[PDB]
Length: 254
Ligand SMILES: C[C@H](CCCC(C)(C)O)[C@H]1CC[C@H]2/C(=C\C=C3C[C@@H](O)C[C@H](O)C3)CCC[C@]12C
Image (cartoon, rainbow, N blue to C red):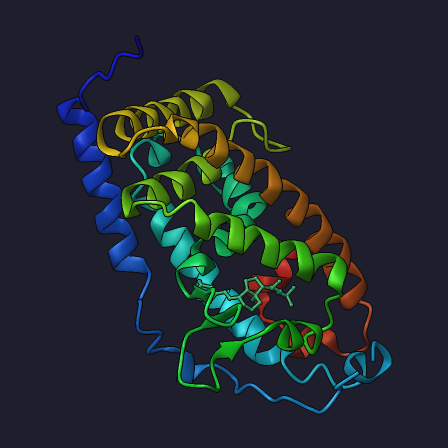
């Protein structure tokens, strides 16, 4: 039974637009990372106290996340439809989705060889231990790694990955959005592009369950977003934390 309509010419052009936007905003060589404040790994082999006392990886990771937010804002601008929104909604959407899109886009440096984000170059291989040296706890980190493994095992085509990031950004149910209807219209155009693509371009397919899986990842990201927000708020109570962050990070997560 299941029909397999072909991608319209407009859908194909959406896909091409989104691949080009990603290629313009995600350097797969990580060649800017040497410009960030450097990573420092104090031995905390075991401690929340040590660690909040040092936050040795926070300057480097905050610069990394700050840089990623900028690339994401650049990616968003190229999403077909996004600029038809009011700038107030554009920013609501970017601010509420930023950490989720960072978590998604980070899947490209994530490796199941050793369960790290390998952006280098050894200095820029990030593990669970680095995330705890930036003041976060296992209640964020463990489900983050689960999410990364789950996403990897979907073996998404790049077309799927960039569509999934766009759909994440353009979510009509973010708090504070005004024109939810327009946002939903933009998102549906993207979601239809993704369903059609999966059905006509993705083999075998007994992965017609792929679309529901991807949608579930969006749900998972929502939970990670609330847990992140909870921890960031506590982290920010550390005296002089702000010096280790950036103005853009302060604004987005504050
Ligand atoms: C939870 C943490 C962000 C915490 C930021 C803070 C401000 C301290 O709350 C995660 C989110 C994404 C994670 C990682 C890498 C992300 C990227 C981003 C992407 O834009 C390029 C590359 O893929 C590395 C591994 C370290 C741990 C990172 C930074």
